[PDB]
Amino acid sequence: MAIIKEFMRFKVHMEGSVNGHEFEIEGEGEGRPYEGTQTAKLKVTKGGPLPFAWDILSPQFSKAYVKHPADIPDYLKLSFPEGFKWERVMNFEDGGVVTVTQDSSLQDGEFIYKVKLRGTNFPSDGPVMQKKTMGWVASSERMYPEDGALKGESKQRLKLKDGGHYDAEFWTTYKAKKPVQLPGAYNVNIKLDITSHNEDYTIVEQYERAEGRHSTGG
């Protein structure tokens, strides 16, 4: 409450590979952790221009910025200053797979994010390697505690240039670096937008709004 301020910056470093293409990204962001909003500016620093869709990377750049009601314990905010780690699997409907590990810490009053990502088995003709995706539809992550960690599961959908859709299932485990209070089951509603980018997506800005709720209705 005194360490997670109402306005917070973060720095993020990602290293990864997708279908064997290695890359690195460095970015900085800022937001309002109790209002559930944040923006980030990412720069490809190695391996650019990326030969695959930016959208598979965008969900990996910050769960300390989820608005929570008072009756749902904010496990990931409570994990600081030590922070938390998370591990994610994204299975896409055409066999593409992305696995991600992340470490979050707080240093000199800013969040520090370290991301490692491996994408594999994307079809050469599919919308990821052909850069045909056009952003994520608004989604809901089902959260529940299990084995001393916070788990989330969600069905996700990318829009496509041809007007169709491209679906994925996300599984994530979030683990605080110290024992803090886990919530019961609840839902996190997320909207993730690419707000600007240059022609080859080597410079990208994102905006995300996230809020935890009991409700399942839209």
Image (cartoon, rainbow, N blue to C red):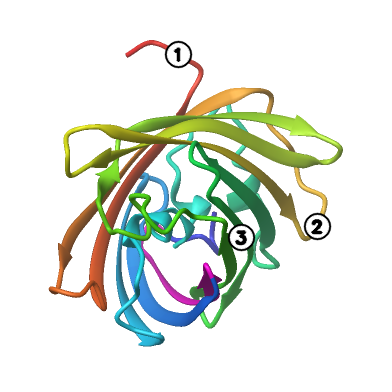
Q: Give the range drawn in magenta.
A: 6-19
Going by the image, does 96 lie left or right of 202? right
Looking at the image, residue 23 lies above or below residue 99: below
- Which amino acid type is marked by label 1? Thr
Lateral position of residue 172 relative to residue 66, left or right: right
Mark 3 nearby-residue class (10 Å; few <14, some 14–19, many ≥20)? some
Quadrant of the rendered image containing residue 114:
bottom right
Label 2: state its secondary structure.
loop
The CA span between labels 3 and 2 is: 21 Å
User: Which residue corresponds to mark 1?
Assistant: 216
Q: Which SS class for mark 1?
A: loop
x and y, in percent, of residue 147 in the image? 86, 37
Query: For this rendering, which residue is in front, 109 or 213?
Result: 213
Q: Which mark is residue 100?
A: 3
Furthest toward the top, the residue is 217
Quadrant in which the C terminus appears: top left
67 or 172, which lies in front? 172
> Which residue in the protein does label 2 denote?
178
